[PDB]
Image (cartoon, coloured by chain):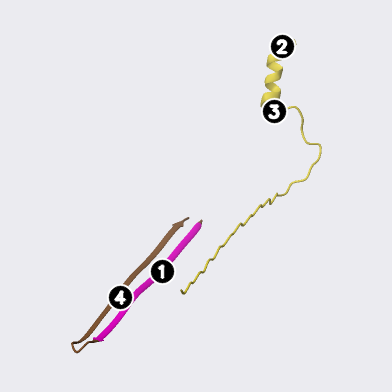
Chain colours: A yellow, B brown
Amino acid sequence: PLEYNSALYSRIFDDFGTHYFTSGSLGGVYDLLYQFSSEELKNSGLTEE
Amino acid sequence: FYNSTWSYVKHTSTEHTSSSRKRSFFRSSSSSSRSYTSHTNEIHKGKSY
């Protein structure tokens, strides 16, 4: 609308957001977390009586 | 994962031996042997992945 109607403008930012890129970089993100946990017990017992 | 393993052996033996010779113009021999064995083996395993 020509007259200010907050709702119908707000729709604009809903649909297209508030800003555009004047410049930027494109590429890819490789993000890895690996976490290994290990635990061993051994028991040996011998009696002669 | 956990992998759990128990192994038990109990070996027991008990023995008795007796001899008794007597002479009094009557002659005698007396003898007793008693042997006991109790043997227990247990193996227990739990494996979860």
Q: Which mark is residue A16?
A: 3
Q: Residues within 10 Å of mark 4 (few under 14, many from 20)?
A: few
- Which residue has dot 4 on it? B35
Q: Pinpoint the chain carrying mark 4.
A: B
Q: Which mark is residue A5?
A: 2
Work out whether A31 lies above or below B11. Answer: above
Work out whether A9 lies above or below A33. Answer: above
- Which residue has dot 1 on it? B9
Q: Given the image, on which type of amino acid does mark 1 rest? A: Val
Rounded to the nearest angstrom, the CA distance separating label 2 from label 4 is: 106 Å
Q: What residue is drawn where x is 67% and y is 24%?
A: A14
Q: Secondary structure at mark 1?
A: strand
Q: Nearer the viewer, mark 4 or mark 1?
A: 4
State the predominant SS element of the stretch in magenta. Answer: strand
Nearest the eye: A30 or B9: B9
Of callouts 3 and 2, the N-terminal one: 2
Rounded to the nearest angstrom, the CA distance separating label 4 from label 1 is: 20 Å
Q: Pinpoint the chain carrying mark 3.
A: A
Report the side of A38 relative to B16 (left or right).
Answer: right
Q: Residues within 10 Å of mark 3 (few under 14, many from 20)?
A: few
| Numbered range of the magenta stretch | B2-22
Q: Give the x, y percent position of residue B2.
A: 50, 57
Q: Nearer the viewer, mark 3 or mark 4?
A: 4
Q: What residue is drawn where x is 28% and y is 79%?
A: B33
Same chain check for tags 3 and 2: yes
Rounded to the nearest angstrom, the CA distance separating label 1 from label 3 is: 76 Å
Q: Secondary structure at mark 3?
A: helix
Q: Pinpoint the chain carrying mark 1.
A: B
Report the side of B24 relative to B40 (left or right).
Answer: left
Same chain check for tags 2 and 1: no
Q: Is residue A12 part of the magenta span, yes or no?
A: no
Seen as rendered, the residue at the extreme left is: B26
